[PDB]
Every structure is written in structure tokens, then in C-alpha cells.
Amino acid sequence: NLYFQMKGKVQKILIWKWGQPPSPTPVPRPPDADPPKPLEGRPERQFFVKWQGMSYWHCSWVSELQLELHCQVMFRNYQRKNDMDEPPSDEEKSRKRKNKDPKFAEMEERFYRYGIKPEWMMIHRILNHSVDKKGHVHYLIKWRDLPYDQASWESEDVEIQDYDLFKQSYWNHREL
């Protein structure tokens, strides 16, 4: 991925940071070469977004240009309310102690430090399911500390804490 993926429609910008420009260095060398480096570009703004209809697991980054081309009205509002030269920053000393767990560390670097509460990515319960013509199943999930109306679908094949434990609960208590 030499560039940012558009996953759907952007719902919200959670945060932004300055970042290095796309670079070609990442293009694999052929197996028949032996013993090239580009000059560093102007940093640009990168944006962490939530997508419409999708849980916090899917939050990813987009470029200023993608926001300009695809959410100009909502991006125009964002720019006018926010400082666009300096980016944004009980809750404190326990982000520290909880972090010595490596799955937490990883989630913290990837998600929580950009404004996602840990609970928002935890299954509260499964509400329903759907099947493709393929037979792949999706589950409509209520997340912890988020309303029912913010329930969202996830593929069965995803890796969320105790996903499978909840699936079995859903399925056991469904013909009772």
C-alpha cells in the first residue's frame, strides 16, 4: 500500500498529525540485482477518520487530498474550527500501568492514543447475523459503552477479544 485506502464514507475526523510524504522506496528489488534513495519531501497532514457504518476497528488514516476531494464540506468545517498548524494532543497513570500488557500496547499505539476508548472496541453482545450466498457470516455487534443505534456489522473472520465466546452465546440462546 503505497497510499491510503478509502474504506467508505468518512463520518468523523478523530485527530490529525504531520507526516512524511508518500515515498517509492517501498517497491521490491528484483532477485537478480546487486549492491536507490530519494530526497525527503515536505511533510503533509494525515487524518485519522471513522468511517460511516463501521466500528472503530476500521479507523484508518487518510490524506488531506482525499478529504479535500471527497468530504469538502465537512473538511471545510473542520479546518475553520481547528488549528491547522499545530495538531491536537483517572485517565492518565492507568494508561501507564495497563500498558505493560503487549496486546494493549499494540492497540494503544494503533487506536487508543488517537481518541478511541478501549471499551468502544469491546463486544457487549451480538444482536443478529447475516449470511452471504457464499456462506460467510456477519454479526451485528453492540459495542461496550456505545448505544444500540451505534451497533455495527463485523465479518465472522475478524479477531476481537472473545469474539468466538460471544458467537457461541448468540447461537446457544437463539432457539430457547
Image: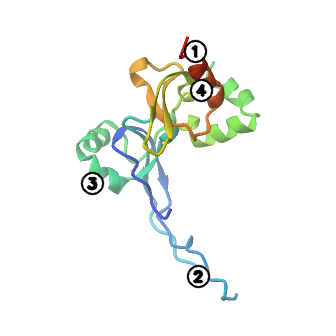
Quarter of the image where the C terminus is located: top right
Disc 1: which residue: 173
Q: CA distance from mark 2 to mark 4?
A: 50 Å
Q: CA distance from mark 3 to mark 2?
A: 32 Å
Q: CA distance from mark 1 to mark 3?
A: 47 Å
Q: CA distance from mark 2 to mark 1?
A: 60 Å
Please tell me which residue is depicted at 50% across the width and 62% down the height of the picture: 1
| Residue 48 percent coordinates (x, y) | 45, 44
Label 3 Cα neighbours within 10 Å, binned few <14 / some 14-19 / many ≥20: few
Disc 3: which residue: 69
Q: Secondary structure at mark 4?
A: helix
Disc 3 residue type (three-letter): Leu
Q: Secondary structure at mark 1?
A: loop
Q: Nearer the viewer, mark 1 or mark 3?
A: 1
Front one among 107 and 153: 153
Going from N to C along the chain, the mark reached first, 2 or 1, is: 2
Question: Up-down: is 127 above or below 137?
Answer: above
Front one among 71 and 5: 5
Q: Is residue 96 visible?
A: yes
Label 4 Cα neighbours within 10 Å, binned few <14 / some 14-19 / many ≥20: some
Q: Secondary structure at mark 2?
A: loop
Residue 159 relative to residue 146: left or right: right
Q: Nearer the viewer, mark 2 or mark 4?
A: 4
Going from N to C along the chain, the mark reached first, 3 or 4, is: 3
Disc 1 residue type (three-letter): His
Disc 4: which residue: 167
Going from N to C along the chain, the mark reached first, 2 or 4, is: 2
Q: Is residue 89 visible?
A: no
Q: Secondary structure at mark 3?
A: helix
